[PDB]
Length: 305
Ligand SMILES: [Cl-]
Image (cartoon, rainbow, N blue to C red; front, side):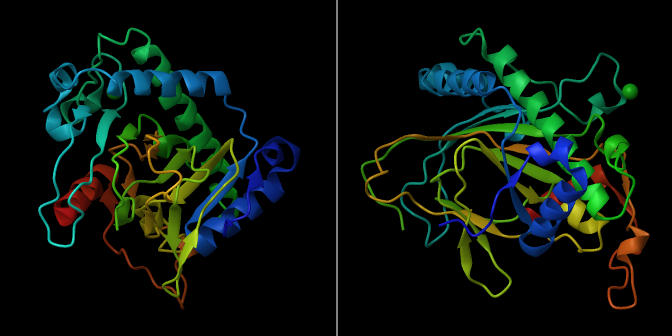
Protein backbone atom coordinates (compact mmCIF):
# COMPACT_ATOMS: atom_id res chain seq x y z
CA UNK A 1 0.00 0.00 0.00
CA UNK A 2 1.01 3.64 -0.34
CA UNK A 3 0.34 6.11 2.51
CA UNK A 4 0.19 9.16 0.22
CA UNK A 5 -2.39 9.49 -2.57
CA UNK A 6 -1.12 10.96 -5.87
CA UNK A 7 -2.19 14.42 -7.05
CA UNK A 8 -2.47 14.61 -10.85
CA UNK A 9 -0.25 17.11 -12.63
CA UNK A 10 -3.20 17.49 -15.08
CA UNK A 11 -4.64 19.81 -12.40
CA UNK A 12 -1.73 22.27 -12.80
CA UNK A 13 -3.44 23.61 -15.98
CA UNK A 14 -7.01 22.41 -15.37
CA UNK A 15 -7.51 23.63 -11.80
CA UNK A 16 -4.37 25.17 -10.36
CA UNK A 17 -6.14 26.28 -7.16
CA UNK A 18 -7.00 22.66 -6.35
CA UNK A 19 -3.52 21.46 -7.43
CA UNK A 20 -1.84 23.85 -4.99
CA UNK A 21 -4.21 22.95 -2.12
CA UNK A 22 -3.86 19.15 -2.54
CA UNK A 23 -0.10 19.17 -3.06
CA UNK A 24 0.44 21.72 -0.30
CA UNK A 25 -1.67 19.85 2.20
CA UNK A 26 0.35 16.71 1.55
CA UNK A 27 3.68 18.50 2.05
CA UNK A 28 2.44 20.13 5.25
CA UNK A 29 1.23 16.78 6.69
CA UNK A 30 4.04 14.44 5.62
CA UNK A 31 6.85 16.57 4.13
CA UNK A 32 6.16 14.57 0.94
CA UNK A 33 3.78 14.56 -2.03
CA UNK A 34 3.20 12.20 -4.93
CA UNK A 35 2.64 13.75 -8.37
CA UNK A 36 1.05 11.63 -11.12
CA UNK A 37 0.49 12.29 -14.85
CA UNK A 38 3.67 14.37 -15.40
CA UNK A 39 4.26 15.79 -18.87
CA UNK A 40 7.96 14.95 -19.06
CA UNK A 41 8.83 13.03 -22.22
CA UNK A 42 9.19 9.43 -20.99
CA UNK A 43 11.40 8.40 -23.89
CA UNK A 44 13.90 11.11 -22.92
CA UNK A 45 13.69 10.15 -19.21
CA UNK A 46 14.38 6.56 -20.34
CA UNK A 47 17.33 7.71 -22.52
CA UNK A 48 18.90 9.45 -19.52
CA UNK A 49 18.41 6.28 -17.44
CA UNK A 50 19.91 4.18 -20.23
CA UNK A 51 22.97 6.46 -20.34
CA UNK A 52 23.31 6.11 -16.56
CA UNK A 53 23.07 2.31 -16.82
CA UNK A 54 25.65 2.34 -19.63
CA UNK A 55 28.03 4.49 -17.60
CA UNK A 56 27.83 2.23 -14.52
CA UNK A 57 28.39 -0.85 -16.74
CA UNK A 58 31.83 0.52 -17.77
CA UNK A 59 35.00 -1.06 -16.27
CA UNK A 60 35.90 0.23 -12.78
CA UNK A 61 39.13 1.86 -13.93
CA UNK A 62 37.28 3.67 -16.70
CA UNK A 63 34.72 4.98 -14.19
CA UNK A 64 37.50 6.04 -11.78
CA UNK A 65 38.87 8.49 -14.34
CA UNK A 66 35.95 10.60 -13.09
CA UNK A 67 36.48 9.96 -9.36
CA UNK A 68 38.06 12.23 -6.75
CA UNK A 69 36.53 15.35 -8.31
CA UNK A 70 35.64 17.99 -5.72
CA UNK A 71 35.07 15.46 -2.97
CA UNK A 72 32.51 13.62 -5.05
CA UNK A 73 30.35 16.67 -5.62
CA UNK A 74 30.89 16.25 -9.38
CA UNK A 75 31.52 13.06 -11.30
CA UNK A 76 31.87 9.53 -9.98
CA UNK A 77 31.91 8.07 -6.46
CA UNK A 78 32.96 4.42 -6.26
CA UNK A 79 31.84 1.67 -3.93
CA UNK A 80 32.99 2.30 -0.36
CA UNK A 81 32.66 1.05 3.22
CA UNK A 82 30.75 2.28 6.28
CA UNK A 83 33.14 1.80 9.23
CA UNK A 84 30.47 2.12 11.98
CA UNK A 85 29.24 -0.82 14.09
CA UNK A 86 25.73 -2.00 13.15
CA UNK A 87 26.40 -1.21 9.49
CA UNK A 88 25.82 -4.05 7.05
CA UNK A 89 28.98 -5.80 5.87
CA UNK A 90 28.05 -4.79 2.32
CA UNK A 91 26.44 -1.48 1.40
CA UNK A 92 27.46 -1.27 -2.23
CA UNK A 93 26.28 1.70 -4.22
CA UNK A 94 27.97 3.96 -6.75
CA UNK A 95 27.12 7.54 -7.75
CA UNK A 96 27.39 10.11 -10.51
CA UNK A 97 26.68 13.74 -9.65
CA UNK A 98 25.86 16.48 -12.12
CA UNK A 99 25.67 20.07 -10.95
CA UNK A 100 24.55 23.19 -12.83
CA UNK A 101 26.31 24.11 -16.07
CA UNK A 102 26.99 27.81 -15.63
CA UNK A 103 27.67 30.21 -18.45
CA UNK A 104 31.18 31.54 -18.91
CA UNK A 105 32.00 34.27 -16.40
CA UNK A 106 29.15 33.42 -14.00
CA UNK A 107 29.61 34.85 -10.46
CA UNK A 108 28.95 31.40 -8.90
CA UNK A 109 31.87 29.70 -10.64
CA UNK A 110 34.19 30.47 -7.70
CA UNK A 111 32.21 28.06 -5.47
CA UNK A 112 30.31 25.82 -7.97
CA UNK A 113 32.58 23.44 -9.77
CA UNK A 114 32.39 22.60 -13.45
CA UNK A 115 30.78 19.32 -14.49
CA UNK A 116 32.85 16.48 -15.84
CA UNK A 117 31.52 14.06 -18.49
CA UNK A 118 32.27 10.46 -19.47
CA UNK A 119 33.70 10.43 -23.02
CA UNK A 120 32.99 6.68 -23.28
CA UNK A 121 29.19 7.22 -23.28
CA UNK A 122 28.77 9.71 -26.12
CA UNK A 123 25.06 10.45 -25.51
CA UNK A 124 25.46 10.90 -21.71
CA UNK A 125 26.05 14.69 -21.61
CA UNK A 126 23.02 15.34 -23.81
CA UNK A 127 20.62 12.79 -22.29
CA UNK A 128 21.53 13.42 -18.64
CA UNK A 129 21.59 17.24 -19.06
CA UNK A 130 18.05 17.04 -20.52
CA UNK A 131 16.92 15.21 -17.38
CA UNK A 132 18.59 17.77 -15.06
CA UNK A 133 16.79 20.64 -16.76
CA UNK A 134 13.51 18.76 -17.09
CA UNK A 135 13.37 17.94 -13.38
CA UNK A 136 14.53 21.49 -12.51
CA UNK A 137 11.59 22.77 -14.60
CA UNK A 138 9.05 20.49 -12.98
CA UNK A 139 10.44 21.54 -9.60
CA UNK A 140 9.67 25.14 -10.54
CA UNK A 141 6.04 24.20 -11.28
CA UNK A 142 5.76 22.36 -7.95
CA UNK A 143 7.18 25.43 -6.23
CA UNK A 144 4.45 27.53 -7.85
CA UNK A 145 1.91 25.30 -6.15
CA UNK A 146 3.82 25.56 -2.85
CA UNK A 147 3.90 29.39 -3.17
CA UNK A 148 0.13 29.56 -3.76
CA UNK A 149 -0.49 27.16 -0.84
CA UNK A 150 1.56 29.47 1.38
CA UNK A 151 -0.55 32.46 0.19
CA UNK A 152 2.41 33.92 -1.68
CA UNK A 153 2.62 35.26 -5.23
CA UNK A 154 2.49 32.26 -7.59
CA UNK A 155 5.93 33.17 -9.01
CA UNK A 156 7.51 33.77 -5.57
CA UNK A 157 10.15 31.09 -5.95
CA UNK A 158 11.22 32.04 -9.49
CA UNK A 159 14.18 34.32 -8.55
CA UNK A 160 14.99 32.18 -5.51
CA UNK A 161 15.90 29.11 -7.58
CA UNK A 162 17.44 30.77 -10.60
CA UNK A 163 20.92 29.30 -11.17
CA UNK A 164 20.33 27.22 -8.05
CA UNK A 165 23.09 24.85 -6.89
CA UNK A 166 20.99 21.85 -7.83
CA UNK A 167 22.32 18.33 -8.31
CA UNK A 168 21.09 15.42 -10.41
CA UNK A 169 22.33 12.23 -8.77
CA UNK A 170 22.56 8.95 -10.68
CA UNK A 171 22.68 6.04 -8.18
CA UNK A 172 23.25 2.33 -8.79
CA UNK A 173 22.93 -0.56 -6.36
CA UNK A 174 24.40 -3.71 -7.94
CA UNK A 175 22.69 -6.94 -7.08
CA UNK A 176 24.44 -8.91 -4.34
CA UNK A 177 23.33 -12.54 -3.59
CA UNK A 178 22.72 -11.65 0.09
CA UNK A 179 20.02 -10.06 2.30
CA UNK A 180 20.59 -6.72 4.09
CA UNK A 181 19.11 -6.04 7.55
CA UNK A 182 18.95 -0.05 1.84
CA UNK A 183 19.18 3.74 2.37
CA UNK A 184 19.67 4.73 6.02
CA UNK A 185 17.30 7.22 7.57
CA UNK A 186 18.02 10.86 6.64
CA UNK A 187 16.51 14.22 5.72
CA UNK A 188 17.44 16.40 2.76
CA UNK A 189 19.18 19.77 3.20
CA UNK A 190 17.99 21.45 0.00
CA UNK A 191 14.75 23.10 -1.18
CA UNK A 192 12.78 20.22 -2.68
CA UNK A 193 13.87 16.81 -4.03
CA UNK A 194 12.15 15.15 -7.02
CA UNK A 195 12.29 11.35 -7.43
CA UNK A 196 11.26 9.37 -10.45
CA UNK A 197 10.82 5.57 -10.44
CA UNK A 198 9.88 4.97 -6.81
CA UNK A 199 7.26 2.32 -7.66
CA UNK A 200 7.96 -0.79 -5.51
CA UNK A 201 11.21 0.86 -4.40
CA UNK A 202 10.86 0.58 -0.60
CA UNK A 203 10.71 4.32 0.18
CA UNK A 204 9.31 5.10 3.60
CA UNK A 205 8.71 8.35 5.51
CA UNK A 206 8.86 8.64 9.27
CA UNK A 207 5.49 9.92 10.50
CA UNK A 208 5.10 12.27 13.48
CA UNK A 209 4.24 9.38 15.79
CA UNK A 210 7.39 7.43 14.82
CA UNK A 211 5.73 4.92 12.45
CA UNK A 212 7.34 4.30 9.06
CA UNK A 213 4.84 4.92 6.25
CA UNK A 214 5.35 3.35 2.81
CA UNK A 215 5.50 5.69 -0.20
CA UNK A 216 4.79 3.29 -3.03
CA UNK A 217 3.46 5.17 -6.02
CA UNK A 218 2.24 3.81 -9.32
CA UNK A 219 4.60 4.09 -12.30
CA UNK A 220 5.02 7.45 -14.09
CA UNK A 221 5.04 9.53 -10.92
CA UNK A 222 7.37 11.89 -9.07
CA UNK A 223 7.74 11.59 -5.32
CA UNK A 224 8.62 15.05 -4.00
CA UNK A 225 9.89 16.10 -0.54
CA UNK A 226 10.55 19.32 1.31
CA UNK A 227 14.20 19.94 2.28
CA UNK A 228 15.71 21.87 5.13
CA UNK A 229 16.16 25.16 3.17
CA UNK A 230 12.43 25.39 2.49
CA UNK A 231 11.56 24.16 6.00
CA UNK A 232 13.65 27.05 7.37
CA UNK A 233 12.13 29.63 5.01
CA UNK A 234 8.59 28.64 6.16
CA UNK A 235 9.41 28.74 9.90
CA UNK A 236 8.86 24.97 9.85
CA UNK A 237 5.28 25.24 8.54
CA UNK A 238 6.41 22.83 5.79
CA UNK A 239 8.47 20.06 7.46
CA UNK A 240 11.65 18.45 6.08
CA UNK A 241 11.01 14.88 7.11
CA UNK A 242 13.12 11.79 7.71
CA UNK A 243 12.94 9.01 5.17
CA UNK A 244 14.62 5.72 4.29
CA UNK A 245 14.65 2.98 1.73
CA UNK A 246 14.16 -0.58 2.95
CA UNK A 247 15.78 -3.60 1.26
CA UNK A 248 13.77 -5.25 -1.51
CA UNK A 249 11.99 -8.54 -0.71
CA UNK A 250 13.60 -11.91 -1.61
CA UNK A 251 11.90 -11.93 -5.05
CA UNK A 252 13.18 -8.47 -6.04
CA UNK A 253 16.69 -9.32 -4.80
CA UNK A 254 18.92 -10.06 -7.82
CA UNK A 255 17.67 -7.00 -9.69
CA UNK A 256 20.01 -4.00 -9.97
CA UNK A 257 18.45 -0.77 -8.72
CA UNK A 258 18.98 2.62 -10.33
CA UNK A 259 17.63 5.93 -9.11
CA UNK A 260 18.01 9.48 -10.43
CA UNK A 261 16.88 11.94 -7.74
CA UNK A 262 17.10 15.69 -8.43
CA UNK A 263 18.07 17.85 -5.43
CA UNK A 264 16.69 21.29 -6.17
CA UNK A 265 18.49 24.10 -4.32
CA UNK A 266 18.00 27.82 -3.99
CA UNK A 267 20.45 30.25 -5.62
CA UNK A 268 23.66 30.44 -3.57
CA UNK A 269 23.20 34.15 -2.88
CA UNK A 270 19.49 33.91 -1.98
CA UNK A 271 18.94 35.25 1.54
CA UNK A 272 16.65 32.91 3.44
CA UNK A 273 14.60 35.20 5.68
CA UNK A 274 11.58 33.82 7.51
CA UNK A 275 8.27 34.31 5.72
CA UNK A 276 6.37 36.76 7.86
CA UNK A 277 3.07 34.97 7.27
CA UNK A 278 4.67 31.88 8.84
CA UNK A 279 5.50 33.86 12.00
CA UNK A 280 2.64 33.93 14.52
CA UNK A 281 2.03 34.08 18.27
CA UNK A 282 1.89 30.27 18.39
CA UNK A 283 4.81 29.79 16.00
CA UNK A 284 7.35 32.55 16.72
CA UNK A 285 10.28 33.13 14.41
CA UNK A 286 12.81 30.32 14.92
CA UNK A 287 15.32 32.06 12.65
CA UNK A 288 15.81 35.67 13.75
CA UNK A 289 19.16 35.77 11.91
CA UNK A 290 18.78 35.28 8.16
CA UNK A 291 21.29 33.23 6.14
CA UNK A 292 22.19 32.82 2.48
CA UNK A 293 21.39 29.45 0.90
CA UNK A 294 25.10 28.81 0.38
CA UNK A 295 25.94 29.73 4.01
CA UNK A 296 23.20 27.32 5.14
CA UNK A 297 24.48 24.63 2.78
CA UNK A 298 27.97 24.94 4.15
CA UNK A 299 26.66 24.91 7.74
CA UNK A 300 24.52 21.76 7.23
CA UNK A 301 27.43 19.95 5.56
CA UNK A 302 29.65 20.87 8.57
CA UNK A 303 26.95 19.52 10.95
CA UNK A 304 26.33 16.34 8.94
CA UNK A 305 30.12 15.73 9.04
CL1 LIG B 1 26.57 36.05 -13.09
